[PDB]
Image (tube, coloured by chain):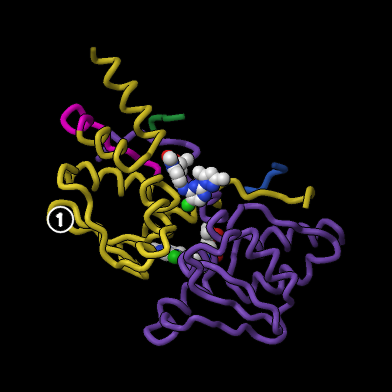
Chain colours: A blue, B green, C purple, D yellow
Amino acid sequence: AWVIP
Amino acid sequence: AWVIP
Amino acid sequence: ADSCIQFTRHASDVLLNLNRLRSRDILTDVVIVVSREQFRAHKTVLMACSGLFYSIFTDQLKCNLSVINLDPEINPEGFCILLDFMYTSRLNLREGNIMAVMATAMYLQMEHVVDTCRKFIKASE
Amino acid sequence: ADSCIQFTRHASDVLLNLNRLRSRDILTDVVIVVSREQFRAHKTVLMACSGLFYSIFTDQLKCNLSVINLDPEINPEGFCILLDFMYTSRLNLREGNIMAVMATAMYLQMEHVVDTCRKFIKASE
Ligand SMILES: Cc1cc(C)n(-c2ncc(Cl)c(Nc3ccc4c(c3)n(CCC(C)(C)O)c(=O)n4C)n2)n1
Ligand SMILES: Cc1cc(C)n(-c2ncc(Cl)c(Nc3ccc4c(c3)n(CCC(C)(C)O)c(=O)n4C)n2)n1
């Protein structure tokens, strides 16, 4: 997996 | 886009 | 074959077009009912994202239903957040909705979402 | 909302599961006929990948057909290679099939595939 898009 | 996978 | 080339953005581009079909109500084939709140979707996308929907739509009797009623304990906002995640890869996780989102993802058998919810709750403890 | 998190591999994971449904013939809803060769698929995936299929299945009469016959000039192998690309992001482009693949992608209105075929042909000249 999870990221800041 | 296009790559060698 | 072993000699294939691959377009990196293809899968993301397909998912965006499936979400555009959902937004315009094009070829939607099921209504999911959550405590009298109704949500239109494509059975194939639901099956690809959820262990519960995979089991439902592979059943020889249930595969033919146009309406599916969820357990009355399920929160409509939690379901809405997960349906948006299915069609976009983006999860709107907030302090005020995390408990309802985790409970809904456990019921829907969405393993990656359950795991992330658990990690975000553990960090606040 | 502006505060969403994003799972990087989600779109690719969804496309793999849609290809698994195609392989097992689960919830396929159309047969594409190419010179007496038949191919089963999901209308939504075809529409997401092709300008021609988007136009066909948004038509108020054609949206209800379970069989679509392509122009007799279309090569079945070229169509097969493009259908596999739709469901996997991988294109099996070879010296022996590139002319048939490019002609089929032009007919199906698949812009990225046409562009790459043109570049690979220009390199051999
Ligand atoms: C060999 C094999 C293994 C799987 C999982 N297969 C499968 N095929 C087709 C579908 Cl539509 C599908 N459905 C599906 C089923 C169960 C799931 C699921 C999707 N998802 C979502 C997983 C991704 C997106 C990676 O998040 C869960 O979390 N579970 C438990 N699964 N086939
Ligand atoms: C605002 C807007 C713009 C588009 C393209 N929209 C669209 N919505 C839904 C669908 Cl199913 C869909 N279909 C579709 C239509 C035309 C296409 C196409 C997909 N594709 C495939 C493109 C990707 C995958 C990026 O390769 C082409 O090449 N053309 C010309 N398109 N909507």
Can you see residue D81? yes
- Picture residue at 62% right of the left edge, 83% below the top: C70
- Residue topped by disc 1: D37
Can you see residue C14? no
Q: Element at badge 1?
A: strand
Q: Quadrant of residue D105?
A: top left
Q: Quadrant of residue C121?
A: bottom right
Pointer 1 local density, CA inside 10 Å: few below 14, some 14–19, many at least 20: few
Q: Quadrant of the C terminus of chain C?
A: bottom right
Q: Quadrant of the N terminus of chain C?
A: top left
Placement of C27 over or under C59, stated as above or below: above
Residues in magenta, as a range: D89-99
Residue type marked 1? Glu
Relative to the observer, which residue lies in front, D54 or C31? Answer: D54
- Picture residue at 72% right of the left edge, 84% below the top: C73
Placement of C73 over or under D67, stated as above or below: below
Residue C51 in the figure: left or right of residue D119:
right
Placement of D78 over or under D69, stated as above or below: above
Tell me residue C7's x, y (percent). 43, 36
Residue C57 in the figure: left or right of residue D33:
right
Residue D103 in the figure: left or right of residue C71:
left
Placement of D71 over or under C35, stated as above or below: above
Query: Dot 1 falls on which chain?
Result: D
